[PDB]
Image (cartoon, coloured by chain):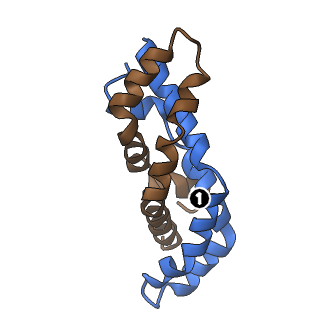
Chain colours: A brown, B blue
Amino acid sequence: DVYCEVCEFLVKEVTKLIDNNKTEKEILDAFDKMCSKLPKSLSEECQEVVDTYGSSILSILLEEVSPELVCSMLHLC
Amino acid sequence: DVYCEVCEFLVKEVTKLIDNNKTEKEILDAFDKMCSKLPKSLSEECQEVVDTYGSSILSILLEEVSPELVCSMLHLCS
């Protein structure tokens, strides 16, 4: 109605907020430790994925956030 | 496909990684400026929402992230 509109607005702002340089820097610094915890037979393919798409994961995941589906879980849409 | 598994792994790790105290704090600090971007006709309903569900928004946002879907955007899955 209008609590859906306000909730949806807020989720959109949050999404925008956290798509920022502090978040990226933090993700990039962690990719090493992330691949290390994987079986030795998957190491190379992990590095290969990180060294191709690592820098673009955050934006892809944020871009897929559905403001109405978040607000649905909060019972506001 | 191992590249699909590896990609999906990475997405889950990133999702966990950003669900932390630095992120929540910056969200909590910014709710006032957010409600101000709204017409004065909606101020109260924005504050009612913030002061009921503001603390829950991050958690729900990341729970809803689909590792599968992100990797398909990356053409590493399906």
Q: Is residue A4 above or below residue B51?
A: above
Residue placed furthest toward the bottom: B40
**Taking the image as drawn, is residue A11 in sight?**
yes
**Quadrant location of the N terminus of chain B in the rendered image:** top left
Q: Is residue B16 above or below residue B45?
A: above
Can you give x and y, in whole percent of width and height, for residue A38 in the image? Answer: 58, 19
Q: Residue at x 45, y 50 (%)?
A: A24
**Which one is nearer the viewer's eye here, A7 or A64?**
A64
Q: Residue at x 52, y 67 (%)?
A: A7
Residue type at numbered disc 1: Thr
**Taking the image as drawn, is residue B63 in sight?**
no
Number of other residues with Cα within 10 Å of mark 1, as a class: few under 14, some 14 to 19, many 20 or more: some
Q: Residue at x 56, y 11 (%)?
A: A40
Q: Is residue B35 above or below residue A22?
A: below
**Quadrant location of the C terminus of chain B in the rendered image:** top left
Q: Secondary structure at mark 1?
A: helix
Q: Is residue A44 above or below residue B41?
A: above
Q: Chain of mark 1?
A: B
Can you give x and y, in whole percent of width and height, for residue B24 in the image? Answer: 63, 61
Can you give x and y, in whole percent of width and height, for residue A46 in the image? Answer: 46, 22
**Which one is nearer the viewer's eye here, A39 or B70?**
A39
Can you give x and y, in whole percent of width and height, for residue B40 in the image? Answer: 46, 91
**Which one is nearer the viewer's eye here, B11 or B55?**
B11
Q: Which residue is mark 1?
A: B23
Q: Residue at x 55, y 42 (%)?
A: B15
Give the total number of marks visible in the rendering: 1
In the image, taking residue B72 as reference, residue A24 lies left or right, namely right
Occupied quadrant, residue A20: bottom left
